[PDB]
Amino acid sequence: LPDSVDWREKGCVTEVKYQGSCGACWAFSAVGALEAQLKLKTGKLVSLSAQNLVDCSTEKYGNKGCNGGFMTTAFQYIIDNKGIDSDASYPYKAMDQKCQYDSKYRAATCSKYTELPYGREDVLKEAVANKGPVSVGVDARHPSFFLYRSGVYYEPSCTQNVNHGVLVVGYGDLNGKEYWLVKNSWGHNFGEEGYIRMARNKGNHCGIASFPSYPEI
Ligand SMILES: *C(=N)c1nc(-c2ccc(OCCCN3CCN(C)CC3)c(C(F)(F)F)c2)cc2c1ncn2C
């Protein structure tokens, strides 16, 4: 395995999104992972519709729109639905709405997803290096996460109980402090211009390897 990876250098990561007051983190995390696989498959980097998940990957998928949901069940929706719309055709509104999916605006498909074994940061590393960005849950229920500005994040009261969906788009180290490079959906002013570097190989810190998954086109 490489010591460091950044999928942004590979042209596989779209712009940071702003979820606002709608708890659609899980939606953005899911489309983020599929965006990278879309680029790898087709040559096109295209922001996919988070809103489509919020409106359509709903009760049947155990999801609750702006009050939270699961990346894995979002992927199954895209599989079952035979498509997800582009973000251009179905833009983000930060609210729960009626499903407005239309196949005429399909930007991606999904054929399968893979759920990584619980707490294994080495298995996560291998997936990030070799497959693509990986959707992850983390514990973001601490003020230090909201206050994060720069560097490698480490919260000693962090648990392995995850409650916020994000996207691991790389890993590396800062002067020997190992990190996961995380794309969040709290807009381009959060942390390092949309990103947070989270402690890696620190005993599954904030549950970052608790529930990892990735899709395939
Ligand atoms: C995002 N803005 C947001 N996210 C959540 C939320 C709650 C719980 C979550 O994970 C549940 C544990 C993992 N499960 C995966 C599927 N398995 C079958 C069962 C276990 C997540 C997740 F998936 F990690 F991202 C997110 C709640 C939110 C929320 N905004 C507002 N609320 C209440």
Image: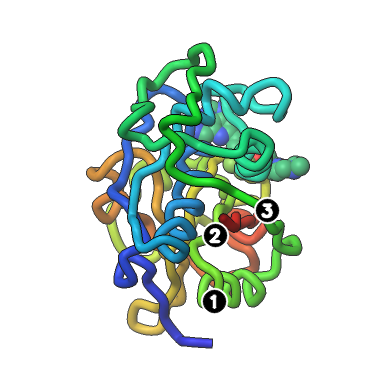
Q: Return the mark for residue 142.
A: none
Answer few, some or many: residues within 10 Å of disc 2's Cα (few below 14, many 20 plus, some between 14 and 19).
many
Q: Which residue is mark 2?
A: 134
Labelled pair 2, 1 in contact (Cβ < 8 Å) = no
Distance between mark 2 and mark 3 Cα atoms: 14 Å
Amino acid beneath label 3: Lys
Helix, strand or loop status at disc 2 = strand
Q: Is mark 2 within 8 Å of ligand 1?
A: no
Residue at label 1?
Answer: 130
Q: Nearer the viewer, residue 174 or 70?
A: 70
* Mark closer to the observer (2, 1): 1
Write the residue at 70% across / 62% down. Answer: 116
Dot in front, 2 or 3: 3
Instruction: Look at label 1 and name its amino acid.
Output: Asn
Q: Estimate how packed mark 1 is, as few (under 14), some (14 to 19) or many (20 or more) residues with alpha carbons within 10 Å.
A: few
Within 10 Å of disc 3 (Cα), the crowding (few <14, some 14-19, many 20+) is some
- Can residue 153 be seen in the rendering of this structure? no
Q: Amino acid at mark 2?
A: Val
- Identified at 65% across, 42% down, the residue is 79
Q: Quadrant of the C terminus?
A: bottom right
